[PDB]
Image (tube, helix red, strand yellow):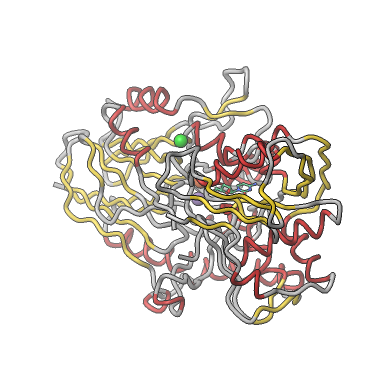
Length: 495
Ligand SMILES: Nc1ccn([C@@H]2O[C@H](CO)[C@@H](O)[C@H]2O)c(=O)n1
Ligand SMILES: [Cl-]
Ligand SMILES: [Fe+3]
Ligand SMILES: [Mn+2]
């Protein structure tokens, strides 16, 4: 018998330094930090030779250190961490697939990705579908895959032109088959399912896709999943497969210890822990911290600039309005100008709280990190209601809306029949009426399954002018945070 230890993360989302989470110790205790995670993994690797560290994608995008470097800083920091293999998540595409190739080429650790291809081609996007990593005489085959639904749902259209993910189940079984007689254990790092709830609290999230995947293939030992940000405090067992995940952002790190007795694909679980990382319990790895610090110094000049103030922490919600959604929608509306009647933006695009006090450029970027450009268009009331119904389905959260738009839905009704009321400036939205709206390019191209945006007429896109520019400009124009932004339930579940 040999201890075989697998440590894993997913959806780290550029949370390179320790930070507060409103629902952990009431936002009063720092969690995570990648230098802390480095210390954890280094200590485990020092204790047992047969120890692997894996990540299931979405290390890009969150705190400004990612967006402002197009993920370059993130690869540099990860190069100081002892990863044995990672896969590619949707967020690694956020600055375009050419940037994906460029940045990830700089990784000093293996990256596996076996089901993204050039459209109308058999050519693979990445060059390595799986790899074998041997430690202390034990060989682990590691496969990387992205779910097709998740890829189409969450990769911005503008960043995936000419590439696509293909049937993840077909490829998973193929790679399991190719590895079967070559390895002791087969692990898949799969980025798939429903996107994470983005909330300061609020919409049920689970790992149903991953259970389905495990039930559909034969011979997979371990399935480490990312995308949903739903941790597995105990492994989910499906046949002989164990499904593992974390709560994202380095809030916790999973550790699985197996008893392996030299019979390939046969093992028992010795111990499992999904451990919450409290910064005050860890010594940060000095090399990782040094690389983070160097990047912060480079970016400081730009990010430190004060752009606004708030009397209270600004929050987000996935199933209803919250202050950051109200603000962003009002900012898009202001930027579009007086011919525009309303603005809509997505809850999943709002990635962090903004603290009370002086608001800085860095804070705004961390909350609104995406290169999603301002778009104006004309939609009918029927098209608007369709978008509202898609929001109310909660598959991708509700749309956040500008002042004057009010929507009430009831989540206990069937999907597609949940909207109860929908008014603009007190008047019901009407099917045939044309409305002048503002949004951004992720939604305009049908992101998050909001298909009706693609039917908009009289479309105008402002190149290079992103949500965070709109927010900064809202304050530059002399607007402030209002009480109705802080407290207005413009979108509400009345269940
Ligand atoms: N360019 C982009 C790319 C992604 N997203 C948001 O990120 C969510 C997935 O984490 C997606 O569900 C979506 O809400 C975004 O707002 N803009
Ligand atoms: Cl999927
Ligand atoms: Fe994802
Ligand atoms: Mn993610």
